[PDB]
Length: 590
Ligand SMILES: CC(=O)N[C@@H]1[C@@H](O)[C@H](O)C(CO)=C[C@H]1N
Image (tube, rainbow, N blue to C red):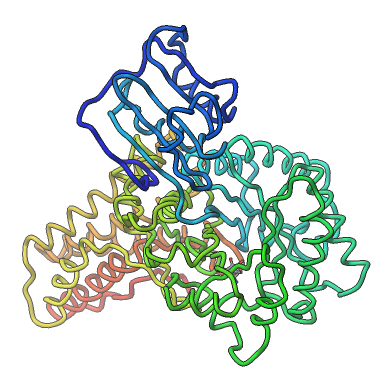
């Protein structure tokens, strides 16, 4: 696969060997970030003056003069070619050249390259991640890892805005970062730059902002401090606030002032972005003037963010048309998936789907708001990178599989198994849901239907359930022990324990269905109760946050099926043996 998939690809069914001996043409004039990647791939392979030509450069460079007609006339666009005669890596701009190298790195398969001609560019101008959730902000190390992941996947945007950073939100938005954090932010900016990512620093001042000179200057002074740390893109967020800070005329005036006195004054500022107080259709007043005021008054270069029809929603043609009409520019999408900050006891590891794939022209930008679990979020982030670069060719399931295989190549099938059953959010105040456990859902439905009305189940279904529980245990134990991405395993570990126990309870409940005799059934029954108590202990010891504490897993299909089957066979046993066993399914000490 190539991820994201390029706009145009012609494959010749030959392959060649990576030289071997090579002449590098343009390494002194091309994007240093791209040349660095190229030289790492060519490591210990000898440059000379005869032997295979490799030309690298940006449109306008001497090295790629011969290829100027093939270089797409798009921002971040590139032309790549591999044949017998030569290799060409030619960006329309410096970032384009870096992107050619990221595709080239994926083509190279143990010393071999396919013979290809690629013409490529993004459909959406700004693509990336807003760290913009409530909860424990991402660690320094996580963020460093994220930035490298973004470059590899051609995301050009990282918006720093954790709701619970005191120097981002109120009241200490007015204060400069202490030295330690300031130095960390400086290093993030440097790393972002190396990976061709725009570090966008957001401020969230609206809960206690006064519309006076004091707070204006404090804000601009903070932006100046961030500038000194290397920050060249900026945002002001007015989401999830009440009070005078919600005044659209004043917001517009503040943003225009920042634009006019700062964004348009510095030698080298890039994005200026704002998130409105009315940030989705349901939170908007169609009879109020809020969004039309922003649309009319905000300077045309300023971006305006949007989460869709609801706080949590997927982006539709009709939804984006509605906002675009009011804000008088293409919305810069803030997509609230996989963010789990309102369903904190769940991991959301399923595919990225639901967003219209034909509306690239109607958005300025598309960023994902991820989980507080940084590594876990890479499944979705990789998919959003693919979707935003090439929406027309976006393939939900293939990209999910490619994401997982990239993140954990040593145990991809185990991670697929875990992720497929850790997808849904459960019921929530936002009404947002995802599919989960789809493959076994008909087998489950048929198995359980057979019980509630009469009987009896198909053997192949009982066996599918059995196969699933077995596979869930292999997956749980192998992931726990995996050392390729330790940060990821640390993140998911509590859920992995709960997932293993779910599978064991499943196996035990299915032995109760097969109930050969009274005492065997009681042995299984007692084992299930013990497994229920073990799940209860994890739910009360792990992930004990103030909001949705604990650890839920395989909640959509698997846990309901196990629990219902348990209750059913206990019912039957109690009839058959005139017994009074407890049929309840969650352990309660009180
Ligand atoms: C603009 C925007 O989406 N703001 C917040 C966001 O910070 C929060 O993570 C989520 C997603 O749970 C929704 C909003 N309450």
